[PDB]
Length: 8
Length: 8
Length: 230
Length: 230
Ligand SMILES: *Cc1ccc(-n2ccnc2-c2ccccc2C)cc1Br
Ligand SMILES: *Cc1ccc(-n2ccnc2-c2ccccc2C)cc1Br
Image (cartoon, rainbow over the protein chains, first blue to last red):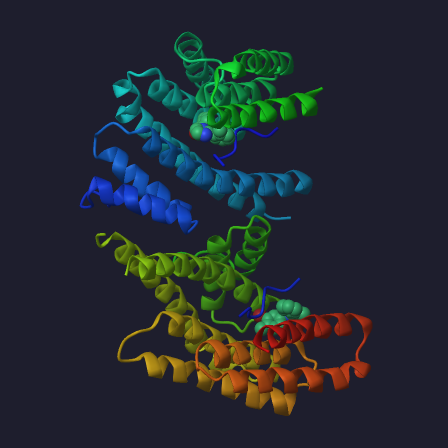
């Protein structure tokens, strides 16, 4: 499952 | 300018 | 260490340059140097630290998963296992370095909710990465270390931060992934994501346009996981 | 060096694993180890060597170009220049390592046209990368070293290889880029690409379907450059 990505 | 890429 | 001679401000400047150059190992080394100067980190600096190490460990995790898959299909000589172990040890080293920075002494000096939650979330994340590759006597203790850090972060965030705060939302997202992927607790994962989403939705009316954009982005990531899991 | 204890076959196996894991620094280290075993490389092994180092230097070049652009816009303190110099020195080190492998002793043992042309093309490419960042007393000598290696490769390839051979085509593509980007010779670049394309086109009728696919791919890259340049 995807966790938090780096900020946009 | 693009040079040779790695092989496909 | 090797960054001891460089000015704090120069380390931060170079971390930003390294990010633009997509030199994440350099970025992490610069930020480790900055932390080791002993001063607290600003919000921007905390985010630089996080981005750097996320990219480094992210590459290692992706490589580990490729190699682990090949190894499990093999089950030839010792090379696949040896190389998986090499990548694993390198990954463990990076996690131990991050955890070391948090313990010496970022968490203990972090008094504001935003900083303390950020660092405890990081602590949970890096124990979670250790858990992903753990198989020995301490594996349950690694999982519990992640859980404990996330839980302390959750308790502080619930008391001190609005339900739309991006750090609070990101924490909940990652803790929910912990539940689903590490702790074998999919129902807890789903409940956490749902309650987080709903409480954030209810508070969006208070936000500026710019804050709304940030909160709703993470809400969408919660919703995406809920869709995957149900 | 550090790979001296590992079997040649294990180094090659691990290079392939590192490629699948997108661990190109590891891949390059494994292939350096394999070269240092002292035996000639097969076709497949030559390609592993090339892929590894292309990826490593490619990342460095991309970072160098980002930093060089920031530096030229700055023209603040010494940090941008210092970090550009750090990346530059690392890049130079990798190029010197590759050139060292070619000189000790890959080229001198390469007797077949395919191997010798491959290595001389590599030699041209890595001198070209050194030329991209060169500014001192030896810059003209660096450019001439690239030119000389490419020219020897061209002379052998014209005598010994069909005009559709992928190594011959790739050499011509890269030498044409040398002319355009390094030697300030756009007309030579264009002429070389055009003649290469045309001579390959004329020989496609001799090829199997699989060889045709390979040759026409590189022909399209020649055509793409001709389009960019005209
Ligand atoms: C753990 C965490 C949570 C939130 C952020 N953050 C800070 C500012 N923007 C964001 C962000 C990050 C990822 C996706 C969306 C948003 C709004 C940083 C970290 Br680390
Ligand atoms: C310099 C060079 C030239 C050609 C190859 N090569 C070998 C097999 N396929 C290819 C290739 C590479 C890039 C694009 C297309 C093709 C057909 C390898 C090197 Br190194």
